[PDB]
Image: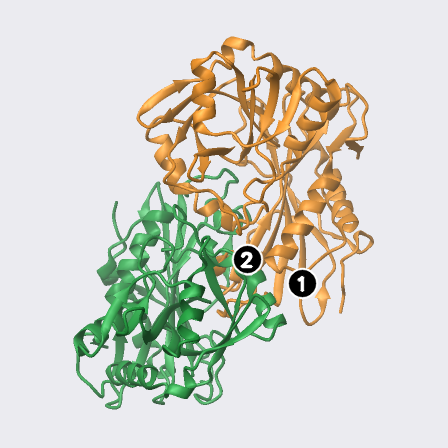
Chain colours: A green, B orange
Amino acid sequence: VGTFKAKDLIVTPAEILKEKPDPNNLVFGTVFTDHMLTVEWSSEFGWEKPHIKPLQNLSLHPGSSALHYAVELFEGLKAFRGVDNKIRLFQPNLNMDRMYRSAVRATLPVFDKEELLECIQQLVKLDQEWVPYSTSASLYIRPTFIGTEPSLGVKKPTKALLFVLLSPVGPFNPVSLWANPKYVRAWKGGTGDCKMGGNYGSSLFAQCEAVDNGCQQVLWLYGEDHQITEVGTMNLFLYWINEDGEEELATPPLDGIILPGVTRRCILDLAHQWGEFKVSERYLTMDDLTTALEGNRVREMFGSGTACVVCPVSDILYKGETIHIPTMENGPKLASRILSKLTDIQYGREERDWTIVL
Amino acid sequence: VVGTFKAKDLIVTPAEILKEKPDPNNLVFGTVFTDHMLTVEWSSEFGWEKPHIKPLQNLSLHPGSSALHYAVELFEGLKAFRGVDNKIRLFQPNLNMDRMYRSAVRATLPVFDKEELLECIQQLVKLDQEWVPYSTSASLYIRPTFIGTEPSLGVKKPTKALLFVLLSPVGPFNPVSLWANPKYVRAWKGGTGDCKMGGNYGSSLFAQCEAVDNGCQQVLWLYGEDHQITEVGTMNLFLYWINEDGEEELATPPLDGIILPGVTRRCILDLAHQWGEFKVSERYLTMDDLTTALEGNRVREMFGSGTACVVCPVSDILYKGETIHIPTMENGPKLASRILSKLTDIQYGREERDWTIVL
């Protein structure tokens, strides 16, 4: 093993810098900044020196294993231009931890998390003017790692590329969910608890079917009893009165088929800290959900992820019926409290160990 | 707007310097590529561009391409064979076009005219025909591949894609030992294990590595509470045995959603049915069915099937700490050899059948 080292960065600035977009009309993942991080690896020579250089197309051998066998993984985190014009990262160490565990499970080569994070900070610092001047926009950071092995054997790659992209993004509009148990996102003994690209390609067909029935996202069901696991690429929370008449924030447990979201983590830590209601990592079925609905026990349902922070759910289509979820008719008080909190930390209105300053 | 590319529109740019062909006896699968490739671009705004045959070159991809982020990708595998009469043949290539088409739909990649793709492939092989080995134990592997090149990071149906085809000469019983650990699952009901989407393969690298450091060559993929035997590496699985009712039987798992429908598998079932010499069954097979059969000396042969190897006999399985011996090689292996001999006779034109296409 070894690692590229940030003290070795080679930097090659763009000649012609691009005009920044309007913060208030930005579609996610659509606009990229001026520069990118690339680092090459080979089993023969190990990790090359890291480059920050102008955003450009990748030159890949058409046999590259990323293209044939989905030898690939990614992350997603954000930079925030704070109320004090200071640029913060949020919980970035948790993303480095996750990206490392993904690399191991993908058989891609390991790296030093601290060195990566310090390369990412130099990238953002170079393009810091792309970090939106706005309190409802951010800069999305997309570390990506791919096998570039030029041979068609299914095997651990002997060549790889780690690269990082920057994209400015903007922004409740509740969501409707499509729940069809014929599709299964992830299985025990599979990779659904890692952020490996192979888990996502198989979802596009279900998403299209979702939009065809006028839903915005897929509710991922699992098992004979139709456990509700995730919502699109978001963790799922239920705020309700449970079977014993207690107020509870519940979310599926990490038993292999749930991606351990940073946002999910932060929300559980906030809820534990507040001490106002029971906080439960536990199994939730559609029948638990509908039984609770025809007893008025449900308050809120929402998804969580880095992109939206929190995403309220208003309806589920299941077995030919639209099932109303009273999230918006209950405020949504919890959802909004969580958003305000996380936003406060992110933009440095509130001071906490969750952010790092550039 | 343009719904399919057409072979009639092919644009050909030959390489200026041709590479030296390898020796067909020292070939490692998928490491040597020929002089030329086929590339066809697509966009949602204009549809399919014209197909190009041009020199093997690196792809220039937007770093946001969805193939790289969300495994919006699929592939195929088929072979060209230089016959005993020196005519070049493809084997069942319309089945590969059909399977690629079905995969594309499940991936949400754009559809294409299957006949047009095959004609472009034929024209690529023709240009590179001297790469088709002068050997009856070697052949030319054809790797059609189809990727999303959508440059935006949203998870969604791609608005840009690339279809490309690589060629790779590949060389020539060497039995395999299998690592069977129920902790890894290849595919599951409600997933995509019945299509050749690249998403299914990247998950398997960890298990394959664990096989190799327990000194096995391949993974035996187990499924479910009862440890169904499903597939071996990237091959379908066959068991030749006396079954529970005491009948000689060739058995292979059914296509219930977790099995890739191999062209080789289909061909072997068709041959077995035509011979009519024993029972042929698409049926569940568990580790307990296997170990019980072995204790009773009822197993004759176990082998994998797939385009690259044709048939790959199994000699041992490591399971729950012990090595379980499979007596394939002590039984000839008669059936495995007869299948290989029949398929290769068809592929290399020793026997004329409509499973092959000349040129």
In the displayed structure, A201 sits above or below B154; it is above
Assess disc 1: are there few (<14), some (14-19) or many (≥20) residues with their C-alpha within 10 Å of its C-alpha: many
State whether residue B125 appears in this view: yes
In the displayed structure, B356 sits above or below B84; it is below
* Amino acid type at mark 2: Val
Q: Secondary structure at mark 2?
A: loop
Chain to which the residue tagged by mark 2 belongs: B
- In-front residue for pair A216/B66: A216
Report the residue at 61% width, 16% height from top: B247
Locate the N terminus of chain A and report the quarter of the image it occupies.
Answer: top left
Residue B159 image-quadrant placement: bottom right
Q: Are marks 2 and 1 on the same chain?
A: yes
Image-based side of A16 in relation to B35, left or right? left
Report the residue at 74% width, 23% height from top: B346
State whether residue A309 appears in this view: no
Report the residue at 58% width, 27% height from top: B309
Image-based side of A146 in relation to B164, left or right? left
* Amino acid type at mark 1: Trp
In the displayed structure, A134 sits above or below A191; it is below
- In-front residue for pair A13/B40: B40
* Residue marked by disc 2: B72
Q: Which mark is drawn over residue B42?
A: 1
Locate the C terminus of chain A and report the quarter of the image it occupies.
Answer: bottom left
